[PDB]
Image (cartoon, rainbow over all chains, first blue to last red):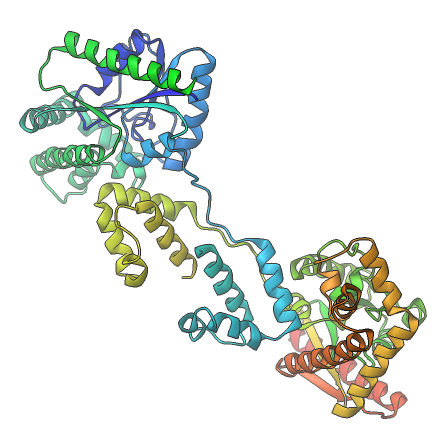
Length: 302
Length: 303
């Protein structure tokens, strides 16, 4: 069993710092689970971790996609899974940090994510069927398990029937995981979120959004993110600059509240309240818990 | 457009002879449309055409697949379509003879025959949706498109809800062709079909089945054919020999009646009655009609 630590939680709770400090005394590398951190050229609107924040700790899945490309949960899982092994090959401890429920669960649970495709074998026996019988017999076979659907297509249209049948056919954690969550009192988290927005505006979020806008990026996953869409409406002349800023802040607060509720609903997640800035004591408490659970799970497995 | 002559009709109506005679005075080649003719070693049970019956006319798609292999309509189409072009490259007229409606229609219509897969983008769209909005919102989405399935899945099971929405989203002639059909009076056709069966028994059908049976062939396309399956029940000891022969004859007649119904239902099929009539006179009538229609369609196309 491969050991994996996951750090989840809303935005602005100190998920980056606690992760770099834990990876330092635990000899680990970080796998980014934030789907927005993958787009290069977009550093401000996405609050991208700086090389100075990594402080030696190697991070992966950052700046690997162009703002015009998409990055689905399947893409994430295909890259992340191999990484966990490659990091272990180095003798380091893999750290999965941040991300939405979809991307995180896809890795910790190793879901299928395979495409929904028909089985060519079944199509063959369906063709052999109409070959031996007729287009009426096949159609009846459809009415014997779905009269409504069959009463919708023409019994002579054996082409659709075979499809309706092939579709009607489709119808009917492995890792040594340790997952912790970082919370914080409501009012405090929101103030840091609003100030986060002012910072982006101060650093030049508007320019960053105009660059993308000018290059013709529109209706893409990158630009639809809850930190670029507000600036786009402004550039479109649909809202005032102050309205967009107020909307961005609100959307970020709504988003953080939604991310907490989600992970708070996840079982097997040990929460830590970061309301107090006493890092030295908390990080030491978190490392002890993580280091311990990994070891007792390893022993139990052995 | 590329020219293509199709000769369709049930079994025992003289589809072979009339086709080789037509191809002689029309400088053509024959493409076998009978899926069973592809399996080598199965000559009797499939009433395979002999080199002598071909009488010089070249035939394709005969004896190209081992009885253990499968041969779908798609396989046939990928082999016939290119062949029609290769026959035209030689300056000959391609003839699609016999076969079941499935194989002939797929060729004369160039059906896509493409697989069915769920667009990876729509799935991406749903995941983004479930993350941008409640998990029950994604549930309400499906509930408005199919409340029955919705009420059948807990809203917290977004994975199963995404699956339902993807499945739902799934369900949301180039040739200058002349098609002729050969028919015959009911009673006459049936008797010729029964005698065809006895002929097979006389030539060695049973032995032919025993060889495929003995080599271990079972539950394959080849052996599931309406002329080898009856013998297999006998060989399995589920039915008496006389019962198999009687059942084979019946299934053979039932299958002819179905083949006729299918083609009779195809528009643009000019029929000809072969009921114990004068051959020399019929073939001459059929050639005139075929040769003429091909030319008037060609002229019309020149416009």
